[PDB]
Amino acid sequence: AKILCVLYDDPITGYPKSYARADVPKIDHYPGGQTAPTPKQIDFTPGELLGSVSGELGLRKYLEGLGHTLVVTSDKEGEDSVFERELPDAEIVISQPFWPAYLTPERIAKAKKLKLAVTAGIGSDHVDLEAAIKNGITVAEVTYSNSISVSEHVVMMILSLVRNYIPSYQWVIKGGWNIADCVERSYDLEAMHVGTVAAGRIGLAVLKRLKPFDVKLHYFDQHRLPESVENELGLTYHPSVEDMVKVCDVVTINAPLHPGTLDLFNDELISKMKRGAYLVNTARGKICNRDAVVRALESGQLAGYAGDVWFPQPAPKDHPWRTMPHHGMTPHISGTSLSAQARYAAGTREILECWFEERPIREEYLIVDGGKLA
Amino acid sequence: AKILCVLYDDPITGYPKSYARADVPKIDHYPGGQTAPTPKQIDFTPGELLGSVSGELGLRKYLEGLGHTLVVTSDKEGEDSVFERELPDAEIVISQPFWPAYLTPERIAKAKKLKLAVTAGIGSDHVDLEAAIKNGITVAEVTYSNSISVSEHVVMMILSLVRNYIPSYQWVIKGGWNIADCVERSYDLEAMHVGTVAAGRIGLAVLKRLKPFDVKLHYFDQHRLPESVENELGLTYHPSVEDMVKVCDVVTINAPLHPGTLDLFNDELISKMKRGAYLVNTARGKICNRDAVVRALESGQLAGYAGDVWFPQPAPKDHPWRTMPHHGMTPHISGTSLSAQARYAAGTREILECWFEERPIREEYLIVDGGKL
């Protein structure tokens, strides 16, 4: 079989020959008890760069050892890409949400041999599930593999915005000291009101990390959490996003993009936030209306915005979120720390081993099971 | 009375006419139960910039209202500073650790009318206690007023170093995307070994905030914490700093400077850390040997260093911690957020009200009272 694997470019300095650290912590399970991936073996040391083209998710020796072919590329856009060229022949497609190979209905139509699409990471946003279902394609993801990573990135961004970290660091590099310049926008987080949109795996990991900073916690979710969980974390539930944001100093978005959440943070909703609110979004770019964010930061309605998701992706050089005031943005990287890569590469191999041995893929990894379909 | 108050300079864009937000949270008490400052009144809105020259810690109208004179300056250095010229005449001196008016033995000897030295913030590192005792000078500080502020700065710095935040943000600014360049040095904090040097007010606040990150916690302190506290936080105690650093992925220094910690993190100790350790220092600059830190970052012995304390302070333009690789430094600002300023300004006023009314200053604020520790 041919496995077609899209990954991001190597670093501009080439695939790394050395790392800052020799190893990473061994993670054996996630909150709630799901076990970390259990492939029969891995052909990498956890800590190596796996998500880029020369990293190959550590899959080449395994796949070629079985007599299969592995094509890896970063070239994935348009009918004229290496991805589209190689697709007709591919039994399996793998990509990450950080550099996704879109499986649109037209590509799936052209993908004559395709039977399994694996997300190396979490989600299936780049795959058209209706066309997958129609064509008997199994869709799998490595559930929970980077949820904790994202939650850390979120809390890091909250603290950096509220405390005015980045401008302060910049004074150091510029040769300055400028205490008053640093601190005329510097606040503590303590006792601020912080709310999350959605309390899934990431939202709940964020609320747990925020709790000992002694903030007051709020959330909105289409499905209200159990009373024991509200009590444990001291959560105030709100029946809507609007109700919630009126009382929050900080708002974090941890929700999927669906009709209910597209352009949720528009001029009007942002106008209902408290003046000088902080808004963090590691969920989906289009949940926050691009220009409404720029406009609110320019007016001071938002005191800061940060997150790692953009529309489109990659962001063009002229994307206005790059130059708007008071942001703490990164590129889309939160779920692809080296620690997370070790987990999702291991889960990718676990899935592939099940596929080739005709053993069931773990139920929690399966988004659509082609084996259940006619 | 003449109150002589030294504060840092206003922003270079001038004293602010407005702020990013309308108010700050009301802090009623601190962990363990100490109440927040209780002045009879305050003349500022919490959230204003109080620690700069035009902010005056919110004191002018109160002091002038009682007939006193208030002299505010940032010019504090040398025998010919405004500070030094006004000192012989001053009944009270106030300064913050972020821009400290040093009360050395020779300065105390010339301060003929000085009877109260207030730290607007925490500690009395800039005050010669021996000279204060000999001269019957009360020395007071606003205990607990910025301990939490520092602990947040520490955790923020740990996360930023570990996840490679600043270089990733710089790719955005440069017009890049460069995922692999960002993440070839990005790790999760979860399940790393993190240790604190000392577990006082700041080090405990730091451990509590790290706990739900699911790190493995370690500490050294001269006074071992109680077993219930250790069990609750899942702390491993180590009998020396050396013993602890050998196992930590991240180390944070939260200890005072005294002969035991002076130059503690030197070439030899840093060499005993795990390769690619992260070291965060918001305690005192000289606890870390300046050049040893630079050498460790240059060789990769340390993967990253961050902190807000420098030697000397303010950091000269040529200080090498400004240009060493893989740092996340700030200037000395952690305990002077606007939120902390609201607390220590209110506590400074509380102390002055007690003083001018001949009522006892809180026991927890007193470092020296009528010739004795």
Image (tube, coloured by chain):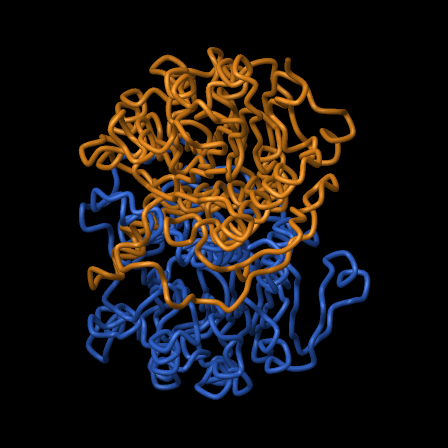
Chain colours: A orange, B blue
How far across and how far down the image is residue B301, in percent?
A: 43, 76
Numbered-mark total = 0
Q: Is residue B50 visible?
A: no
Residue at 46% x, 79% y: name it: B287
The correct choice, above or below, for A118 with respect to B287 in the image is: above
Comparing B320 with B122, the one in front is B320
Give the image quarter of residue B260: bottom right
Residue at 61% x, 36% y: name it: A143
The correct choice, above or below, for A42 with respect to A130 in the image is: below
How far across and how far down the image is residue B119, in percent?
A: 45, 64
Comparing A219 with B223, the one in front is A219
The correct choice, above or below, for B273 with respect to B28 in the image is: below
Residue at 32% x, 25% y: name it: A293
Q: Which quarter of the figure is the C terminus of chain B placed in?
A: bottom right
Q: Is residue B206 visible?
A: yes
How far across and how far down the image is residue A30, in percent?
A: 68, 44
How far across and how far down the image is residue A311, in percent?
A: 32, 26
Comparing B27 with A219, the one in front is A219
Give the image quarter of residue B3: bottom left
Comparing B251 with B170, the one in front is B170
Give the image quarter of residue B98: bottom left
Residue closest to the far right: B228
The correct choice, above or below, for B344 with respect to A107 in the image is: below
Q: Which quarter of the figure is the N terminus of chain B placed in?
A: bottom left
